[PDB]
Image (cartoon, rainbow, N blue to C red; front, top):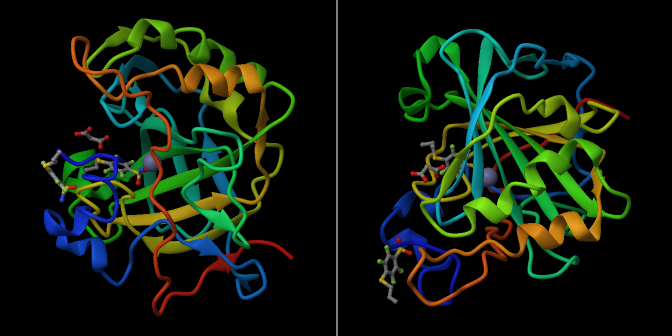
Length: 257
Ligand SMILES: CCCSc1c(F)c(F)c(S(N)(=O)=O)c(F)c1F
Ligand SMILES: CCCSc1c(F)c(F)c(S(N)(=O)=O)c(F)c1F
Ligand SMILES: [Zn+2]
């Protein structure tokens, strides 16, 4: 199985998923000085008022909150996107210590963690079929820095003890993902990929400029999770991030400055 260790981590993924060495892999370093301000980009429209979270689970590579995406309830549009994308899940990537954890970097800076709110293009009817298309998914990426607590994250942090090992899950209703957003929706965008196997090149990335702050106690709880299933050797779930990949011919566009 793929993972993040020395023997099954990012440098090994290309042997099962050759698109790892593709032309539009993610994440990337965002060079804020070469990114092109595009005055034609729209404001992002984040419409999460009717979101319905359902469950939270530890899948062995992160923890994920899944939403009811069977109706048009929590949708992303505007910005660089054509059409309408529906929120299906969010998850995080984070480090073994505060100076690393994010997948995207900004001028080579790593953040403590990165939140991925994952949406699929409604013209493809559902998430799996969307992941097979070059404009199938839109992932809103938000950086986490350690400082003051994010009140809206606490409901997530407080349930993680119940999903410590791979395969555990719990009901998780009435979680409002609006409480995980920073004030500004200024963003960078570029065409890329899933950052884990199968690494499909199906993602329009929209990475917010403004990080959210979370507390040390909040991120500490992420680090208590385990990659392993209950009954296997204990390997804390930390450093579940893919390093920056070559930008190749791509431009990163900015909605601002
Ligand atoms: C302890 C030995 C691990 S076996 C293995 C592996 F090495 C990989 F690199 C992969 S990969 N190419 O998906 O990382 C894999 F799926 C594996 F099962
Ligand atoms: C087939 C799509 C389901 S798999 C998946 C995913 F949904 C992501 F959001 C990501 S991410 N980490 O790019 O947001 C990912 F890497 C995945 F592999
Ligand atoms: Zn992710």
